[PDB]
Image: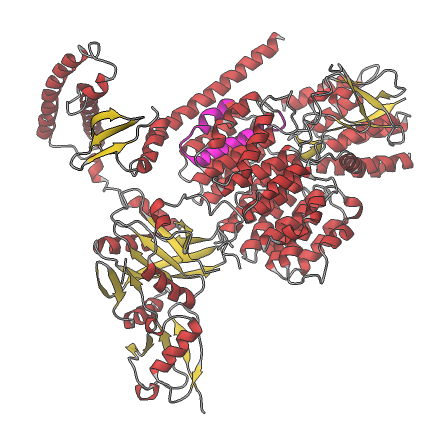
Amino acid sequence: AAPMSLAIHSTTGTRYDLAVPPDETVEGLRKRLSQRLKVPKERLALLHKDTRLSSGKLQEFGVGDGSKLTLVPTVEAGLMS
Amino acid sequence: PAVDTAEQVYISSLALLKMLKHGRAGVPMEVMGLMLGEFVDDYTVRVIDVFAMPQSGTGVSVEAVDPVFQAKMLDMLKQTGRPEMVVGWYHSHPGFGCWLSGVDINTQQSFEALSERAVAVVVDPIQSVKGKVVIDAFRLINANHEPRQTTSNLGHLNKPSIQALIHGLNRHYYSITINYRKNELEQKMLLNLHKKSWMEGLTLQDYSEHCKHNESVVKEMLELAKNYNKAVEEEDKMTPEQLAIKNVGKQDPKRHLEEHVDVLMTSNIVQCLAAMLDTVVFK
Amino acid sequence: QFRNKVLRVLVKIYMNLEKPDFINVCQCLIFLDDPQAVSDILEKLVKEDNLLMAYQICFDLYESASQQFLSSVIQNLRTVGPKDQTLKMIKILSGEMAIELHLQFLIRNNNTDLMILKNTKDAVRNSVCHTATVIANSFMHCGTTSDQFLRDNLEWLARATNWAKFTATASLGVIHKGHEKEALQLMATYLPKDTSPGSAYQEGGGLYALGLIHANHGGDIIDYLLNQLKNASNDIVRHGGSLGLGLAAMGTARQDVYDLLKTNLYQDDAVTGEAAGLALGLVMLGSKNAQAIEDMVGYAQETQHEKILRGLAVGIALVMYGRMEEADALIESLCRDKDPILRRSGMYTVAMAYCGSGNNKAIRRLLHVAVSDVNDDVRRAAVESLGFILFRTPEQCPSVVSLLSESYNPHVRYGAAMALGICCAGTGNKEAINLLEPMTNDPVNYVRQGALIASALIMIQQTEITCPKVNQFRQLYSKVINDKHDDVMAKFGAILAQGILDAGGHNVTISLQSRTGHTHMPSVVGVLVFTQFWFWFPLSHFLSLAYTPTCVIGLNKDLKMPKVQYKSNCKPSTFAYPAPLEPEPNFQLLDNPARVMPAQLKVLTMPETCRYQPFKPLSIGGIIILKD
Amino acid sequence: LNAKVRLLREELQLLQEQGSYVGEVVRAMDKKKVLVKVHPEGKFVVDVDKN
Amino acid sequence: DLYSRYKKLQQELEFLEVQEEYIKDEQKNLKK
């Protein structure tokens, strides 16, 4: 398995540390974080070296064990839509 | 498992000015931002500083455009001595009062899932006037009873407004008391803004302008006295109700005379005292 | 100074007489604060066979003498010692007797219309009203060792949760006021261990009740509570234990309790710190300790939890009790502060320093703050303090709060209401009620709440004859509580007011000053701290202190009840219970012990046919030894 | 002065109540109703208060 | 007796002075 033990720092300070398989994809991490937080996956946005993780596998982006990941949710306001 | 009703959110002076200015900047738009602070006790949620955020939207919705800014700015601010981390979000309702809508509730719900005691602050720039500022802090009631427990009257002192109730207050979200506590140096500078230099205190006026102003006001008082005469003769041949309408659209001599007399007498007293005080001080 | 001199000369005179009145001279010495002199005079008495006069003097000393003075008197007595007589006077001076007798009186005469509580319960819809009705019960059964309402309706009591359990448990200690005989076992029943474990709230409430059982009266409970507070783990239990210890060692400037309480305060926790601050206040009462005062002021200027700030605000004020002009430096330092809560502590300090003296300068300061300050809570605290200054001349409080009740600021309105409440306590003035009527329908809710509680305080125990407007106010309470269109805070106020109106059975009144005229320090402390339910509901169990029995009690030579009977020269209807809710004899006969109003004394008469003869005139009332 | 400040402080809610239309009465009729033209809209048959 | 009336009147005078000063302060602040 060799789980990739990462860190998930939130902009609020809390730390949802979690470990994932090597072949995980940013979509998979988003989805697991959404289950843990009970928030829709679209509202989340992961960060690494000031560079959003748009999509695709984690490895080729470079995300590795003992990494720093910032979890930043969306911010929306409006009467409708 | 309480969230007492004595819980308050402490907004600093700088945070308030930042929110208000950012909101007035985007008058027709629901501009928004983040707020940094700490979680001290179950009765205090202190908001220290805020920072605007890159964004784009229409008059009916607004949304963030980059999170890189959020993480980067947190790191830079932390470098120079403000480690505090985010405690909620704020936005501006320009003329709609202060309440939360569905989209607002959705974003606030994500934040609350991130951290339990997160708050939402709403400002209304155009509704705020010189003295008072229209503002309020909220949080989400779950689907469970009473949302919070009571151990004081600190919750029930505000009489929530009809518009906020109509739009969901006390049904989906509940308010929190806002405290504007300030330290000593903040107090000392807030008192020091309106203070002019010392020279302005001992400067006379262009005396020619003084005389012109005096003669102008007295030439006005002449006609005001004539009208005062023409108006005191009435008030006997006028019905007790009719008088309440005598002064609508028609100048009243009495009040204007009072105003002009106060103006003339203050201005002349101040100029005289300055002239004498100088006459002594400088040799 | 001159008043002291004159009182000395008067004492000299009272000494030179054919029948020197020893009650009067002992009162003169108390006021003169010379415990050595009373020690000597009481030695002289015990030497000669005047044991009845010595006993009455020991009674009067206990009723209206400061703890420090009484401790000095007992020390002096022990310096010389009649050893059996000596020890019986020791027992009287410890207050064990008087407290026990008052307890007996309270238990015997316990008519309580439970139908009213049943109606209030039927009207309950939320948790505020729930705790309101619990506290109101606690007031109805104050000291009467009866807990039927909490017993029969046990399921309804479980509804309360978290802190509402703290209050509901402390209600037990309030109900068993003075029941020193056996407390630890008593509380153990209602605070069962290993029963529903995981309730620090329950333990805190239990300790609060335990302390509440021993107001102003220390003993072994002091040591036990200190042991607990030293073994506490949960912050909640620290809070409870600190409050209990404060209520357990009032006025006794014990250094070890001060050290422990200060160690807790220096934790920088909120809910523990509030209790710690109030406790430091209640312990070092009266003492002008510069050390404790500076610790308070520094901490209040260093902490960041408004809860600690509130606790300290009342603690500091408690420290300076009884000092007329010696607090002026502290008053000025606090008033010119910038933190609002410290300014509030300053107003409270002015209140407690000039308690009853009517010092016009303290009034000037409080009124100037009331009209001139920018914070609203300071305004409210200022208007309220006026009540403490001017309570010896109730004719003057309306004169200086009528205009202030009709004020744009709601908090000032509430302050005027509660100031009238404290100032005119147990008097039933027509004027006070005339002011309290129109504003019981004030648009703002907490104003209504304060108005109802103020009325219940003023018109305690009065019947239909004494005040025409009592029935109106009972009906108003019922209508407010049953109604549903009205706010919750108003319902809380009405419930507490029903509790107040008929307290401790119907045989207890609130008298800031003893019947002689001395300021009753526990009453002042209780009515000040109870007033702080606007910040912490569990503090509402402090008007328990103000509850002083309205009893006329006869005693025999060996201090045991004689079955005497007395004459009440007024119609049986008036000066009696109003009624239990669903030719006039020109005299009525009361038995021993007697539920006697304060006013019923001016018309209280003894039947000369009876063999006994009271030592001192009945009219002063209160505890009386009887001669034969 | 206190009354003046209180009135000013309440005036914010009093000024958020709705208004009242101005109608021209055509003829009182029936038990207590009136027929009122509400310029520019049409006529109505409205009730009359107690006072 | 007349001594008591005298002291009563004098204290009434002090109280009236205190109240007058307080009302002046109240008016000045109510203007603001």
Residue C37 is inside the magenta segment: no
Give the percent coordinates (x, y) of residue E32.
Answer: 32, 32
Residue C406 drawn in magenta: yes
Residue C147 image-quadrant placement? top right
* Position of residue A59 measured from the top left corner of the image (x, y, whole percent): 34, 88
Q: Position of residue C523 (x, y in %)?
A: 65, 35
Quadrant of residue C36 within the rendered picture: top right
Left or right relative to C365: residue C591? right
Span colored in magenta: C399-427
Secondary structure mostly taken by the magenta-highlighted segment of the chain: helix
User: Considering depth in this image, is B90 or B201 the residue closer to the camera?
Assistant: B90
Question: Residue D28 is drawn in which quadrant?
Answer: top left
Residue lying furthest top: E2
Q: Is residue C248 in view from this perspective?
A: no
The colour mode here is secondary structure
Residue C422 versus residue C312: which sits nearer the camera?
A: C422
**Which percent across, then down, holds residue C503?**
67, 35
